[PDB]
Length: 97
Length: 26
Image (cartoon, rainbow over all chains, first blue to last red):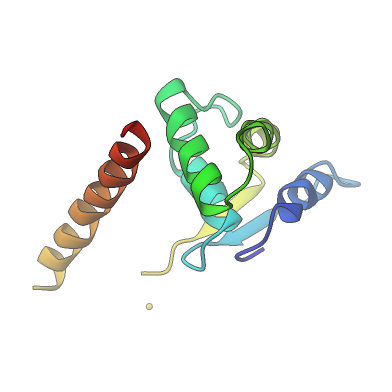
């Protein structure tokens, strides 16, 4: 997954809980939702345990980068926590060889 | 210069994040 709109978060959830569950590698650098998946995966503890400072920080970057409503930004943070929880299937291609 | 540019890129990333958060606060 690269770049990717609001839809790719639910697509990551649909592929995270797949039959059987299958990995979702996300290449960062491009931006948009792949970068909030990456900025989760870097430092989100036990996946869905994004802490409170990140809560406000992630919700600022969602409500600013996606330009969506604040309720939708909180809701995509909850779907993000659902997807982030299974981060062992998530891999990030941090470019920079 | 390559390793010290890795300093400047990481440090300024915190500068861009703090400026964006201060814009939300004000």
